[PDB]
Length: 53
Image (cartoon, rainbow, N blue to C red; front, side, top):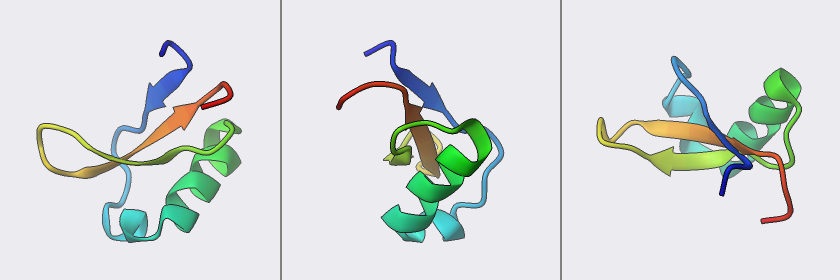
């Protein structure tokens, strides 16, 4: 899944809405979705995906 890019230094509270995360991801990196993901720090991170799921 190379089509994935983890967001670093991004508000987690905002990730509370799969709508904001994906939206922000595109507006910033212009990906396809960019939903939130739980990493090791348990912090919601937006993973900008540049592909078809």
